Image (cartoon, coloured by chain):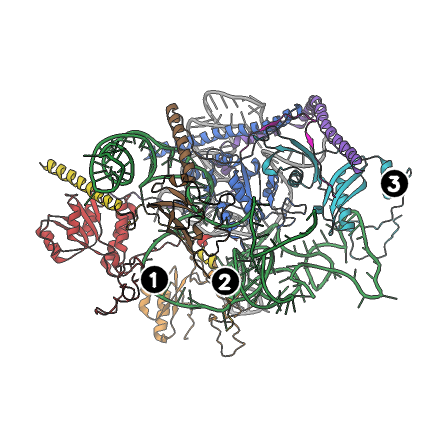
Chain colours: A cyan, B red, C yellow, D brown, E purple, F blue, G orange, H green
RNA sequence: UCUCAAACUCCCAAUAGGUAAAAAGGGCGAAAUAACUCAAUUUGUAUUUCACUCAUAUUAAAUAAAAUAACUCCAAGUGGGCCAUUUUUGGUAAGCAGAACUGGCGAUGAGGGAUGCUCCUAACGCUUGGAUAAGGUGCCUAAAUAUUCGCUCAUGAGAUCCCA
RNA sequence: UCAAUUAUUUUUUUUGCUGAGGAAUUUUAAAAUUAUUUGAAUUUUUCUUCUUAUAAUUUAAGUUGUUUCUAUACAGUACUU
C-alpha cells in the first residue's frame, strides 16, 4: 500500500534439495529463511549459501519451496537482535546489533542504512546471520534502553515542511518555529 | 537499432532485362515473359530467362549434337535457346524438328532438304504454349577460348589453364617452371 | 628506418566478412596417388565390368531387333 | 624465429609418465578400412611418419592405406579458408575414431526399436531430445529431519 | 488461351490498426468464443451486492477449520526455525571457549 | 462458380465453429491447470510429505541493450535468437542448450515465465506475422485468422487462440508457430528502470537476467 | 515549417543554399557537395547549412504540382493548344520567354477558348 | 624440517581447438568382374547389376530476416595506422617501445561525461506524437530547495569512471 | 471492519495527438449490433448463449457531419510570399 516510508526488503523461507543420483540415492533437503528485495534475489542468496556450505550449485539441486514469511503482530513493536558478518575495505568482521522495530524486515532495512551510513558498507558486503526477537532487559544499546522507560513524553522539536501545494515561494511574514 | 545481416536486403544478381535495343528480341521476350508468368510450368520461365542472357551464354548448338540427342526422342520437338550450326564432319541428316534462336542458312537448307522442320520461337509459342512433349536444349558453356585461359595460375602445381602467351614463337614460354631442366616444373 | 613489426589485428575480422570457406565435399576424387597393382587391377575390373555391361547391352539390343 | 620441422614440441611430443618405451603389438594389429574416420594420436617412440604439430589429436577420413602407412584427409585452417590436406601417418599414430561408434550403436538400437515399432504398428520418435523438463515431485523427509542452514561467520 | 491461367488478384491497400482488445467485431473475428466469455463475466457482474453480502459470511465460516489447521502447519514450520536458532546459539556458546 | 464459393464459405464458417470448440477445451484446461496448482500446494501443506510442481516449459526473453560494441559470440547468439532490435521480446523453448545460449547473452537481456494474461495480451496488442514466401516474408499485423490458418494449416493450428495456447505452454506444434510470428517489437517501459546496466539478481538495484514471473509486470509496463 | 495546401503537402520551402557562401565571396549560392575532409557538412556537425536530401522529395500524387492545382506546360506556339484542350482540367499554360506580342495575344485568346488561364497572363502588355 | 623457479614438473583448470549427429547415403542379402588376394575362381578385398528397407504425413539434438548462398570473371582502393578493457614483454618509469584477444576510432553524426576524435549511452532519409536510455532534478540549465535513515564543521573541508 | 499481495477479469472519469485511402466485384464475404424467426443450451438471463431463416445498419470495411468565417472581396493596412 504505502510508498512514502515503505521498505521493499521482505523475508522469504526457501527450501531446496540435491537431485537424486546413484551416489545420492537419498538426498539431503536444506531449508533457510532469507531477507531480500525480491524472489530472484532471495533465491540467488539461498543458492550462494548452498554453494558456500554444500557442493550444490543451481544445476545440482531442485527448489522445493520459496515463500514470503508473514508478520504475526505488525502493530506491536519488538526488540530485534541481529548478528552480522560484514566486509570492510581492509578486512572482514562479525558484529551483533540491537534494533527496536515492528518487524524484522524494518530492522534489516535499518541495519543496511546504519552500516552504509556509519561504516560505508554496501548491502552486497553485509551478511545477516540470524535476526530474532529478544527480551527488552537483554538489550545493550542505550538508545533503546531510553525507549523502554516507564514514562516517554518528549517535546517534538522539528521543522514544519507541509507539502507542494502550500509550499509557498514567498511569504508576507516570517514563520513560527515552535508551532504552538 | 535493429541488427541486420546484409542490411536486410536481398541483393541477388544477374540480368534485370534485355539490354539490347533490338525490336524483335524485345518483342520476343515480352511474349515469353507473358507466357512464363501465366503458365504453371517451369519450361516457359527457363526459356524466358535463357532468352535474356548474354552473348557468351548464347553459344551455338551443333546440328550433330542435337541429332545425337533427339534419336532417343524420335518424334519430338527440340527447342534451342541459341543458334544451330551446320557440320561438315556430318555425312547426312536423320530428319529433325528444331526450334532455334538463329539458323545458319546451310543448316536450315539441310533441315528442309532432310524434310525436317524449322521453327521460330513465336511459331513454337503458338503451337506448343504449354511445352508438353517438347525438349529443351542448349549448347556448350565452357567451350569458349576465354574459359580455356580461366582457372588456376599458369606454372602453379596441377594447373592446366592456357597462358595469355606473348606470341606463337618456339623459344618463348616453355622454359622456367614449365620444364624441370630450367629452374623447376609445375 | 625505425619500423613497426607486426600485428594479427583485424585479419580474423576480415576473414569473417566473407566467412571461412570450407570443402566442396565431392563423392569422387582423382586417384593418381592411390595404391599401384591394386588400382591397376581395379582398372582391369572396371574395364571388365564395362565390357560385361557392353556384352549384355549389345546382345540384348540385337535380340530385341532380332 | 627459426621454423624447422619439430619447432615448439618439447612439452607436446614428451612421453606421458609410466608409458615409456615401445608399446604393445596388439595396437598395430587393429583393422582399418577405407572411409573410416581415424584420430591421429602419436606415441613418441617411432620417429618415421611423425605428422606435423597441428594434426596431433585431429580426426579425419582414411582415404588410402599402404604397407605401414595410412593416408588421412584432415582439415586445416589456412588464414581465411579451411582446406583438406593429405596427412600420411603410421599404424603407430592411428586411433580408430569414436563418434562413428556412437552413431553405429545408436543405429543398432534404433533398428531394433524400428523393428518393434513396425511389429506393433505404432510410431516412435528417434530424436535425442531436450534436457530441462522436470515433472512434479515429492519430498518425504520427516519435518524435523530436514537440514537447517545459516551463513558462515569469520575467522 | 486454353494454356493461359485465369487472372489472379493482388493484396489489398494498407488498413488501419483496428484494436484486438477494444474493437468488438475484430475481437469476435479473432476469438469467436469471446461472446460466451463476455457472458461469463456479465453473469458474475449481474449478481448484485446484497447476494454477495449474504454469501460472504458463509464462505468465511466454512473456511475456518482449514484456516486453523493451515495456521498450525505454518506455526510448526516456525517451530523448526526457532529450534534451529536456539540449537545454533547454544552451540556457539559451547564452542567459543 | 457460386456453389463452389458458397461451399467454401460454409467450410470457413465450420472452421470458426471448430476453433470455438478448441477454444472452449483450452478455456476448461486453463482453469483446470490453475486449480491443480492450488490443490497441489494445499495437499503439500496438509501432508507430512512436501511437494513441488513441474517445469514451466517456455521462457519469454526481452532484449535491453543497443547493438553498438557487441562481442562476436554474442552477435551470433543474438542472430540465432532473433533479438535483433533493442526492445525485441520472444518466446523460447526451455532446454539446456537454449538456457546456455541465453546465459551467454544474459547481460543484454531480461527473461522469465510470462503468464497467460500477458501471453494473450502481447499477441493480441503487438502480434505481427511473416506473410510472404520462404525468406520473402513481410510484416503484417494479424487482424484475421484466415491468413495464419493458411500457413499453419498444414501443421493444423488454424486460429490465434491455438497460437496463444502453444506459446503459453509448449506443445506438439511450437517451433513453427514461434518462428512464423514476427519478433515482438516492444515499447520502452512507461515508467522506466532503476538502472539498465545492472542485474535483477544484484543487491544493487538492477534489471537484467532472470525476472521470472515478474517479467509480466515489465511486459505490461512496456506494452 | 511544412506547407500543406489541400492534399498537396510540400515538405520544405527554404532552398538548400550552399555552405558558407557569404564567407568566401567567390562562392555562388547554388548547391555544390563538399569533397573536403572535415567539411562540417558531410562530417555531420549540427548547426551548419543543411545538406539537401532525397527524403525532402515530393509525394507521388503531387510530384511537380502547383498551388494552381494544374501541372504547368510552357507554350511558344499556337499549335500547342490541341493537346492542351484535352488536358485542360489537369494542366495549365505558361507562355514562353521569347513570344512576340501579336502571337502572344493570339495564344492568350486561344487559352481563353480552351478555358485555361495563363499563369503569366499580364506579361508583355 | 623452512622457503622456493619465465626458460623445473608428480598432479592439474577455466578459456580456446577438433571430429559427430543418415538418402548422390546407410543397413542386410543375392548375382556378376580381377592380371589384386589366401592353401582355397565366395578364401577374402573392392567394384558393378539386381533385391529386400531406414526417420523425414512436423524434419535420425537444438536454434536460425538459413539462397542476403554458391561459383566464375574482370578490376579498384590499401600496404606509415591509432585508442580502450583484459592478458602482457622490455625498460626506473613514461600520454614510452613491443606483443595477444576483442571492441572502437580511422571512415561517425547524436545525447551524456562542466569542456574534450576515442569513456558511457547509442550508430543517422524527411516529419508528427509518445515513452524512455545514458544521465540528471539549488541556480546558471530542463525536472524535487522531494521523501527517507545514517554519518560529516574543516584558521586552504568535500563533491560524477577515464580525469588532471 | 472486510486489509494487503498475487491471479484471471470487467469497467470508468477527464482528456492529448492522428485521419493515409478512395473499393468498373476483397469497402467483398462472414462477424458485430438492432428489430424480427426457428431449434436448442446453461452459469438463468431488460448487453444469456449457440444455429435456422429475414431485414436493416456499424463496433465490420484507413473521418465524417453541422455551423461559422474568408465575403457578399477584386487587392487593402487583411490574405499569399
Are the residues at dot 2 and dot 1 in contact (C-beta closer than 8 Å)? no
Give the quarter of the image for residue D94.
Answer: top left
Q: Can you say which quadrant of the picture contains the C terminus of chain D?
A: top right
| Count of numbered badges drawn on the protein | 3
Q: Is residue D15 above or below residue H41?
A: below
Residue A145 bears which disc, if any? 3
Residue F116 shown left or right of residue E51 in the figure: left
Marks 3 and 2 belong to one chain: no
Please indicate, yes or no, whether residue F163 appears anywhere in the rendered image. yes
Q: Within 10 angstroms of label 1, few (less than 14), some, or many (20 or more) residues?
A: some
Q: Which residue is mark 2?
A: C7
Image coords of residue E26 (percent x, y): 49, 38
Q: Nearer the viewer, residue G3 or G22?
A: G22
Give the quarter of the image for residue A133.
Answer: top right
Image coords of residue E24 (percent x, y): 52, 37
Q: Nearer the viewer, residue A134 or H36?
A: H36
Marks 3 and 2, how far apart at CA: 71 Å
Q: Within 10 angstroms of label 2, few (less than 14), some, or many (20 or more) residues?
A: few
Q: Seen from this angle, which residue lies furthest front?
A: D21
Residue D44 shown left or right of residue G88 in the figure: right
Helix or strand or loop: what does disc 2 sit on? Answer: loop
Q: Which residue is mark 1?
A: G85
Q: Using the image, name the chain to which the residue with label 3 belongs.
A: A
Amino acid at each position: 500500500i504505502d510508498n512514502s516510508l515503505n521498505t521493499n526488503i521482505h523475508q522469504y523461507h526457501i527450501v531446496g534439495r540435491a537431485i537424486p543420483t546413484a551416489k545420492d540415492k537419498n538426498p539431503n533437503v536444506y531449508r533457510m529463511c532469507i531477507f531480500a528485495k525480491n524472489d530472484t534475489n532471495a533465491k540467488s542468496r539461498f543458492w550462494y549459501f548452498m554453494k558456500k556450505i554444500n557442493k550444490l550449485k543451481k544445476s545440482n539441486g531442485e527448489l522445493l519451496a520459496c515463500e514470503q514469511i508473514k508478520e504475526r503482530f505488525p502493530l506491536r513493536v519488538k526488540n530485534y537482535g541481529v548478528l552480522l558478518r560484514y566486509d570492510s575495505r581492509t578486512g572482514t568482521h562479525n558484529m551483533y546489533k540491537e534494533f527496536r522495530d515492528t518487524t524484522k524486515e524494518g530492522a534489516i532495512a535499518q541495519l543496511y542504512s546504519e552500516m552504509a551510513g556509519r561504516h560505508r558498507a554496501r548491502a552486497s558486503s553485509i551478511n545477516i546471520i540470524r535476526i530474532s526477537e529478544i527480551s527488552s532487559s537483554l538489550v545493550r544499546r542505550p538508545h533503546i534502553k531510553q525507549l523502554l522507560k516507564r514514562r516517554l513524553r518528549f517535546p517534538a522539536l522539528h521543522l514544519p515542511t507541509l507539502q507542494k501545494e502550500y509550499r509557498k515561494k514567498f511569504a508576507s511574514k516570517r514563520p513560527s518555529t515552535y508551532r504552538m | 537499432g535493429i541488427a541486420l545481416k546484409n542490411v536486410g536486403r536481398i541483393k541477388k544478381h544477374g540480368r534485370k532485362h534485355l539490354v539490347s535495343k533490338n525490336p524483335y528480341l524485345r518483342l520476343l521476350v515480352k511474349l515469353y515473359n507473358f507466357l512464363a508468368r501465366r503458365t504453371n510450368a517451369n519450361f516457359n520461365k527457363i526459356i524466358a530467362k535463357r532468352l535474356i542472357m548474354p552473348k557468351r551464354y548464347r553459344p551455338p548448338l551443333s546440328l550433330s549434337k542435337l541429332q545425337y540427342h533427339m534419336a532417343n526422342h524420335p518424334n519430338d520437338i527440340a527447342v534451342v535457346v541459341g543458334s544451330i550450326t551446320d557440320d561438315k564432319r556430318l555425312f547426312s541428316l536423320k530428319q529433325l524438328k528444331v526450334c532455334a534462336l538463329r539458323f545458319t542458312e546451310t543448316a536450315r537448307k539441310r533441315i528442309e532438304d532432310a524434310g525436317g522442320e524449322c521453327l521460330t520461337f513465336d511459331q513454337l509459342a503458338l503451337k506448343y504454349p504449354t511445352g508438353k512433349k517438347c525438349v529443351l536444349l542448349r549448347g556448350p558453356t565452357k567451350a569458349r577460348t576465354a574459359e580455356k585461359h580461366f582457372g588456376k595460375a599458369p606454372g602453379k602445381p596441377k594447373s592446366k589453364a592456357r597462358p595469355y602467351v606473348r606470341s606463337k614463337g618456339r623459344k618463348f614460354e616453355k622454359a622456367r617452371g614449365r620444364r624441370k631442366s630450367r629452374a623447376y616444373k609445375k | 628506418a625505425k619500423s613497426k613489426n607486426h600485428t594479427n589485428h583485424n585479419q580474423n575480422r576480415k576473414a569473417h566478412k566473407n566467412g571461412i570457406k570450407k570443402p566442396k565435399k565431392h563423392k569422387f576424387m582423382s586417384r593418381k596417388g592411390l595404391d599401384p597393382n591394386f588400382f591397376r587391377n581395379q582398372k582391369y575390373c572396371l574395364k571388365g565390368i564395362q565390357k560385361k555391361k557392353k556384352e549384355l547391352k549389345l546382345k540384348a539390343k540385337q535380340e530385341k531387333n532380332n | 624465429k627459426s621454423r624447422g620441422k619439430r619447432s615448439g614440441t618439447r612439452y607436446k611430443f614428451s612421453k606421458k609418465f609410466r608409458k615409456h618405451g615401445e608399446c604393445t603389438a596388439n595396437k598395430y594389429l587393429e583393422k582399418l578400412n577405407y572411409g573410416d574416420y581415424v584420430d591421429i594420436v602419436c606415441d613418441s617412440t617411432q620417429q618415421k611418419g611423425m605428422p606435423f604439430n597441428y594434426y596431433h589429436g585431429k580426426t579425419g577420413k582414411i582415404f588410402h592405406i599402404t604397407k605401414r602407412g595410412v593416408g588421412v584427409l584432415v582439415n586445416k585452417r589456412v588464414k581465411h579458408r579451411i582446406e583438406q590436406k593429405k596427412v600420411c601417418v603410421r599404424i603407430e599414430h592411428v586411433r580408430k575414431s569414436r563418434c562413428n561408434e556412437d552413431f553405429l550403436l545408436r543405429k543398432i538400437k534404433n533398428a531394433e526399436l524400428i523393428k518393434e515399432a513396425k511389429l506393433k504398428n505404432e510410431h516412435i520418435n528417434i530424436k535425442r531430445k531436450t534436457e530441462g523438463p522436470k515433472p512434479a515431485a515429492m519430498i518425504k523427509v520427516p519435518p524435523s529431519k530436514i537440514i537447517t542452514i545459516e551463513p558462515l561467520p569469520f575467522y | 488461351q486454353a494454356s493461359l491461367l485465369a487472372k489472379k488478384k493482388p493484396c489489398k491497400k494498407r488498413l488501419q490498426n483496428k484494436n484486438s482488445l477494444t474493437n468488438f467485431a475484430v475481437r469476435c473475428r479473432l476469438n469467436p468464443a469471446y461472446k460466451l466469455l463476455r457472458s461469463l463475466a456479465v453473469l458474475r457482474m449481474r449478481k448484485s451486492i446484497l447476494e454477495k453480502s449474504k454469501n460472504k459470511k458463509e464462505k468465511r465460516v466454512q473456511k475456518q477449520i482449514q484456516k486453523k489447521e493451515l495456521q498450525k502447519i505454518n506455526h510448526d514450520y516456525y517451530k523448526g526455525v526457532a529450534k534451529a536458532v536456539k540449537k545454533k546459539k547454544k552451540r556457539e556458546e559451547k564452542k567459543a571457549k | 462458380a457460386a456453389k463452389k464459393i458458397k461451399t467454401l464459405k460454409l467450410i470457413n464458417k465450420k472452421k470458426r465453429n471448430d476453433l470455438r470448440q478448441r477454444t472452449l477445451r483450452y478455456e476448461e484446461e486453463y482453469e483446470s491447470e490453475r486449480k491443480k496448482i492450488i490443490e497441489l500446494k494445499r495437499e503439500a501443506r496438509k501432508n507430512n510429505c512436501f511437494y513441488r510442481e513441474a517445469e514451466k516449459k517456455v521462457v519469454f526473453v526481452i532484449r535491453l541493450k543497443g547493438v553498438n560494441k557487441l562481442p562476436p559470440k554474442v552477435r551470433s547468439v543474438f542472430r540465432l535468437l532473433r533479438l535483433l532490435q533493442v526492445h525485441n521480446g520472444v518466446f523460447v523453448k526451455v532446454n539446456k542448450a537454449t538456457k546456455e545460449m541465453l546465459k551467454i547473452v544474459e547481460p543484454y537481456v531480461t527473461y522469465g515465465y510470462p503468464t497467460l494474461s500477458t501471453v494473450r495480451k502481447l499477441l493480441y496488442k503487438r502480434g505481427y506475422v511473416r506473410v510472404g514466401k520462404v525468406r520473402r516474408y513481410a510484416r503484417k499485423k494479424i487482424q484475421d485468422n484466415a491468413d495464419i490458418s493458411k500457413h499453419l494449416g498444414k501443421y493444423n493450428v488454424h486460429g490465434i487462440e491455438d497460437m496463444v495456447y502453444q506459446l503459453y505452454t509448449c506443445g506438439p506444434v511450437f517451433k513453427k508457430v514461434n518462428n512464423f510470428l514476427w519478433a515482438f517489437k516492444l515499447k520502452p517501459p512507461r515508467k522506466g528502470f532503476k538502472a539498465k546496466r545492472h542485474a535483477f539478481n544484484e543487491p544493487r538495484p538492477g534489471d537484467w537476467g532472470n525476472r521470472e514471473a515478474h517479467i509480466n509486470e515489465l511486459i505490461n509496463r512496456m506494452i | 515549417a511544412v506547407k500543406k495546401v489541400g492534399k498537396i503537402i510540400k515538405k520544405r520551402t527554404k532552398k538548400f543554399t550552399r555552405f558558407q557562401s557569404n564567407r568566401f565571396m567567390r562562392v555562388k549560392p547554388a548547391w555544390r557537395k563538399p569533397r573536403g575532409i572535415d567539411c562540417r557538412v558531410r562530417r555531420r556537425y549540427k548547426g551548419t547549412n543543411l545538406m539537401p536530401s532525397i527524403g525532402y522529395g515530393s509525394n507521388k500524387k503531387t510530384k511537380f504540382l502547383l498551388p494552381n492545382n494544374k501541372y504547368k506546360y510552357v507554350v511558344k506556339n499556337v499549335k500547342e493548344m490541341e493537346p492542351l484542350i484535352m488536358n485542360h482540367t489537369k494542366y495549365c499554360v505558361q507562355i514562353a520567354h521569347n513570344v512576340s506580342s501579336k502571337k502572344r495575344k493570339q495564344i492568350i485568346e486561344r487559352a481563353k477558348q480552351m478555358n485555361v488561364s495563363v499563369i503569366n497572363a499580364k506579361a508583355r502588355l
